[PDB]
């Protein structure tokens, strides 16, 4: 739906 | 932080490290990413990732609104799952960390954008346009299917709009100086005109300084001086098309008496506030519907004189003198004197922050 | 490069004011100019914003319909037209600038201008001695800020604690200045708006 | 949409060389669009951090920022003597741009005994028609203190800034009163 | 019949056999004449006859009305009285008879007009012009003086305005056929346009037939078709000057549907009745103030590519198609399709009657 | 190549007429079209002229202000608008063409049209026998021209001398037809406008 | 300006093969802008000469013209049988373009005796109320003749064209008269 | 003044 964000731990 | 998108079914998810890939003319930043798949519910056993450069554009003959024709200018595909023994590629610094976080069910993919390719340029839509953006825009597509030729399902694919951008060079070039000399009929004395911009490279919103020097030795009087900045765009889809559009014009009522000189400095600034209604104007690549500035000039690959696809945007400054009429020939001759000054209009290379999408959203 | 604004002052409620921020060192097409107000003793607040490149202007909900912001690109100045000012609108207004390409915070700020909205007029300060250790002197029912308070014409600068003025319920300011003397004078008070220098002595 | 940025603590004190951390919380996700400012009393705010992690040019490297979900942290490694000011938290992802409440950082000193002085109204108050009494509290640390009035609201108090000579606060709470009520007791 | 003019003093009289000298490109008809002098009252003892080709033209800087600057393009002189032993030339058939009639006090003179010379062309004066005709006009001057450098007296000279004219060639040339093909951007299908006049050589007042063939295969629709006849004049006084002036335009509202052909025949006729107000239009050489038709085309000396002085007049027919706008680029591009058809406009060679001067005078 | 004109006829004095000369074989820009009228039994006279190339029109002094000439280049026709016609304007009108470059006389002429301006109306002819050698027959008080006169229904074509008709002072035409018979009938008279065929016999 | 072109003779007669000359005079100089026309009875005029000396195309070479000052002459070498018509003189140098009076050329024949016949009004004239008498002159040459009326203007006469059979004219002069005047004598 | 005409006899 929508481009989300996330961190590479 | 990295950007992730998931399929409507939720089985497919792709991770991208950025959305703007800078073009260094000779080389282009590679497009790396990680695709997360779940083979337990995936019976197709094949996952394909495709990078597509298409010239999406509307149709005037068709009365249907929104429908557009897609013409691919560059298509490349790489299969990630299962891991192809022949498609063995090195892993980038960000790519290896993403695999570690996700687990053993994530596989990478990497594309190499070839040079001599168009940059993301979106033409300004009209007030009655309701479809998608028109122009050149890249796209990263990931899907799983039994074969390439198999029909694609809307619930079994993801797509992200990426961009290819260029920034202002570090080294300034020579100052653009152009001069002209017009010889009339009544007398042999010439009408000289000189113009020179302050510097070759200008930024978005930075004022443009024009120096005008007129050495009139004829018998006629110059009535008006017109200074304008025009956007030159080259589109090569099936045949080369050239069109011009003035983005900032300033008219001065300066009058030069015969056998007298003249010198003045003019300031101009192109901006989008007064160019909203100019349909067809070229703007920088939009993601979905954001506001973007005027399209920045494209750095062509030296003097290769190649026929680059897509849209090539260039700018010029025109200095025009209006000469009084009358006498023998009357209003039949064209005695206007003009000269053109090319210049480059780009963005400085950002330090850390990439271009953002409407930072203060309404 | 510097941002300087002028036009602040005392205005009756329901009046109007013109704040002009003469931006120097940069233009208005490549920079977005913002107005930020800070109430006395309170936090910052954003009231207006203008983007001359895209021709977009934004206002806060509190000042919507009363505040008008516009930019004069000829001399690189941005104006803030205020109408129907109220008592709660008294604050210190700052002119801020942010990069148009792209937003990275309000890096450049103005020196600050003070806007006071009160129905009261100019009033003369009243000096009352404070008998006793410590010695004090109270000044009340005056307007507007500030007042200069000194002891013994500047000869007593040790142990003096001039406290910040406060706003009373009647719309008038007041403050107290105290000094400590162990065993053992002159409460020099000056008000620039009323050009009055009242001095008093404190005795038990 | 509006975003309320809850900044805690409201105010703290620390000594020179101490590690100071400030927490900023957003009611909604704001990605990494958060900036930090430092405003000394009487001057304009100075930009310190933008994008919640990028240090502004010209700012000493002791300042640092971090992001973890919706919790933004401004951390000072060594508390230099010139770092004692008020810090505000900003978000610039959605209009309107909302600021934080602000946090006051002051020097740390040992406990000081509050000396309580009472000043009765002078003889000049008799003809003025207004009666006011001010209690004085000098050289007390920390700022928080308790005041009791007796001979009931309508009381005004003022606090001076920390004087560099003594590093202590001063309190002066005054109570105006009518002539009829003042003479009652 | 021959034409004679006498000096105001009556001592000098010159006879000319005609006033129009036809130019055959390779050779020009010689200018012969007889000068009658009376040496009894003539003490200068020298008689000089001068042929002058001058570009008389007004001045716009000077506010004085009527005053013009004279620039000679070709000056030749021959002395008749006394008979020069070195200037021995053969006598034409008409010249010998004139001497017999006048007597022994009449002496001849003969000039040879060199080729590569301008023809008599007079630009159309404006409503506020009160001076002499502007353009190229020859003149035959006869006078008696002690020396060439001596000042000339108004009472001791005569002047006649002669002309150098050209007529239509006997052999017609190839039919002027020109075609164009415009390629658009949306589709690769071309938009063809053809045009062809009936014959190369047209006469003054004769209608001009234009055949238009449009083979539209694109998606756009042609709105209007414009047919015009334009007069191209080249003036070389100090620098080459090019200007154009439409003398007959006809606009048709024909619309061509996409994927359809079109064929029509248009008739045009240039004339001076509707071109009275077009100041600067080139007309055939006037003697004093007569009405003359549009300037006839000049027959250049093959492909010598020489810089001929004076005024060179040529004609063309332009076929222009107006293409509907809209779509992607909007009103920025220029999609008009045009083609030009040159043709020759002269007079047939008269049998016996030379051109006359307002035969039914008012 | 041919010039043909139409529109002539009988018109009351003070009326109007339209003569159209449909030029065929050439145009009107390269040719100047002239109108020439010839009164019955008189010489030629020039009334109008038009030059479409230079846009100049000329009229005679007699017909100045009453006659208007114009050309329709679409179909190569020239018109002559006549107003306030008088009795002296009756004549035969010819359409003539002359070369524009250049004038060399009226080489091409029209076939001719007859315009009659009279206040009288149509009247029936009256046939009266002429008794005696020669035999005659007089026809008078008729209008308009012409009338057909024959003897013995065309059987007597020898010795017949039909004289041209003349205009009387009353506005009516009359003529006499005579024939010579040595020793020894039928005066066949027909009038087309009145469609009347009156025959009379002549006896001593 | 107007130019009156006097053309003489008014009419002449000549035989076949005779040389016929016609003189045209102009009141003012008209250079050499003179044209000649030939109009047979009932037909349109035909152009013969233009510029007073140039023979029109298609015209037989027997026709010729000449100029001497203001006197213009049209000369026919051999009088062909088809040359018998009316000739007009034209000038086209000044507006208005003026024509000549015209000259009639007819065949030549010997003198013919004029037979005079008188026709009294018939009995039908009695009831009509109008009285008219016509005198007949048949087969007389040349055209000019003298008529005498007796039993005074208001008399009308008509002349027929030369009949090819007899080459003679016919005269019929009529005199209308009132009933009262007719019965007077 | 004016260009006259004449014939060569």
Image (cartoon, coloured by chain):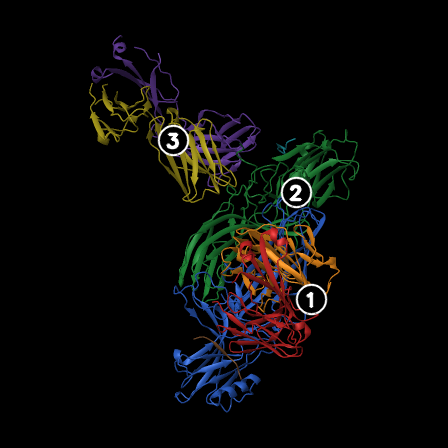
Chain colours: A cyan, B green, C yellow, D purple, E blue, F orange, G red, H brown
Where is mark 1, residue-wise?
E174
Q: Residue furthest top?
A: D184
Disc 2 sits on a residue from what chain?
B
Report the front residue among D56 and B235: B235
| Tally of marks | 3
Q: Which residue is the site of mark 2?
A: B60
Front-most of residues B260 and E269 = E269
Locate residue E306, reporting x and y percent: 58, 72
Q: Which mark is residue C92?
A: 3
Q: Quadrant of the rendered structure where residue C20 is?
A: top left
The answer for how far apart the CA atoms under marks 2 and 1 are is 42 Å
Asked if the residue at tag 1 contacts the one at tag 2, i.e. Cβ–Cβ closer than 8 Å, the answer is no
Query: Mark 1, chain letter?
Result: E
SS class, disc 3: strand
At 73% across and 42% down in the image, what residue appears? B77
- Relative placement, left or right, of D87 versus E248 is left
Asked whether residue F143 is in view, the answer is: no
Residue F5, image quadrant: bottom right
Same chain, labels 3 and 1? no
- Pointer 2 local density, CA inside 10 Å: few below 14, some 14–19, many at least 20: some
């Amino acid at each position: 739906s929508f481009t989300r964000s996330t961190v590479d731990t | 932080r990295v950007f992730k998108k998931a399929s409507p079914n939720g089985k497919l998810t792709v991770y991208l490290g950025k959305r703007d890939f800078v073009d260094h003319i000779d080389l282009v930043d590679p497009v790396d990413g990680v695709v997360l798949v779940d083979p337990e519910y995936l019976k197709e056993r094949r996952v394909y990732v495709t990078l597509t450069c298409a010239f999406r554009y509307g149709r005037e003959d068709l009365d249907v609104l929104g429908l557009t024709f897609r013409k691919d200018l560059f298509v490349a595909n790489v299969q990630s799952f299962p891991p192809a023994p022949e498609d063995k590629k090195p892993l980038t610094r960000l790519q290896e960390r993403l695999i570690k976080k996700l687990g053993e069910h994530a596989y990478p993919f990497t594309f190499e954008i070839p040079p001599n390719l168009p940059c993301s340029v979106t033409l300004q839509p009209g007030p009655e346009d309701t479809g998608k953006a028109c122009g050149v825009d890249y796209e990263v597509k990931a899907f799983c299917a039994e074969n390439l030729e198999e029909k694609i399902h809307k619930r079994n694919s993801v797509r992200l709009v990426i961009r290819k951008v260029q920034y202002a060079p570090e080294r300034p070039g020579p100052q653009p100086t152009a001069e002209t000399t017009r010889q009339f009929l009544m007398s042999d004395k010439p009408l000289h005109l000189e113009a020179s911009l302050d510097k070759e490279i200008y930024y978005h919103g930075e004022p443009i300084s024009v120096n005008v020097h007129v050495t009139n030795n004829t018998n006629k009087t110059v009535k008006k001086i017109k200074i304008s900045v025009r956007q030159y765009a080259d589109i090569c889809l099936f045949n080369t098309a050239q069109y011009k559009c003035p983005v900032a014009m300033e008219e001065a009522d300066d009058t030069v008496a015969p056998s007298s000189t003249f010198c003045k400095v003019y300031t101009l600034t192109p901006f989008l506030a007064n160019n909203r209604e100019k349909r067809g104007l070229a703007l920088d690549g939009k993601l979905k519907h954001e506001d973007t500035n005027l399209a920045s000039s494209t750095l062509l690959r030296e003097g290769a004189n190649r026929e680059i696809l897509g849209i090539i945007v260039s700018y010029k400054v025109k200095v025009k003198l209006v000469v009084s009429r009358g006498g023998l020939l009357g209003d039949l001759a064209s005695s206007d004197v003009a000269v053109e000054l090319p210049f480059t209009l780009m963005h400085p290379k950002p330090k850390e922050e990439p271009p953002h999408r409407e930072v203060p959203e309404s | 490069v510097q941002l300087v604004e002028s036009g602040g002052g005392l205005v009756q409620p329901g009046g109007s004011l013109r704040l002009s921020c003469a931006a120097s060192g940069f233009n208005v097409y490549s920079s977005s100019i913002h107005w930020v107000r800070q109430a006395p003793g309170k936090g910052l607040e954003w009231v207006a914003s203008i983007s001359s490149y895209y021709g977009y202007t934004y206002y806060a909900d509190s000042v919507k319909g009363r505040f008008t912001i516009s930019a004069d690109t000829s001399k690189n100045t941005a104006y803030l037209q205020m109408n129907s000012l109220r008592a709660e609108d008294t604050a210190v207004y700052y002119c801020a600038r942010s990069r148009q390409f792209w937003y990275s915070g309000l890096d450049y700020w103005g020196q600050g201008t003070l806007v006071t909205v009160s129905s009261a007029s100019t009033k003369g300060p009243s000096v009352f001695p404070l008998a006793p250790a410590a010695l004090g002197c109270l000044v009340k029912d005056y307007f507007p800020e500030p007042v200069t308070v000194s002891w013994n014409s500047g000869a007593l600068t040790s142990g003096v604690h001039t406290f910040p003025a406060v706003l009373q319920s009647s719309g008038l300011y007041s403050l107290s200045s105290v000094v400590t003397v162990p065993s053992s004078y002159i409460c020099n008070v000056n008000h620039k708006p009323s050009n009055t220098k009242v001095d008093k002595k404190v005795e038990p | 949409s509006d975003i309320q940025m809850t900044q805690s603590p409201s105010s703290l004190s620390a000594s020179v060389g101490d590690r100071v951390t400030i927490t900023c919380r957003a009611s909604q996700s704001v990605s990494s669009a958060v900036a930090w400012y430092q405003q000394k009393p009487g001057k304009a705010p100075k930009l310190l951090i933008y994008s919640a992690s990028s240090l502004y040019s010209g700012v000493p490297s002791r300042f640092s920022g971090s992001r973890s979900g919706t919790d933004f942290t401004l951390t000072i490694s060594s508390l230099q003597p010139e770092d004692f000011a008020t810090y505000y938290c900003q978000q610039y992802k959605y209009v309107p741009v909302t600021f934080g409440q602000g946090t006051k950082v002051e020097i740390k000193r040992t406990v000081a005994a509050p000396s309580v002085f009472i000043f009765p109204p002078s003889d000049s108050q008799l003809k003025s028609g207004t009666a006011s009494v001010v209690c004085l509290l000098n050289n007390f640390y920390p700022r928080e203190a308790k005041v009791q009035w007796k001979v009931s609201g309508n009381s005004q108090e003022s606090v001076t800034e920390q004087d560099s000579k003594d590093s202590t606060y001063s309190l002066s709470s005054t109570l105006t009163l009518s002539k009829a009520d003042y003479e009652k007791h």
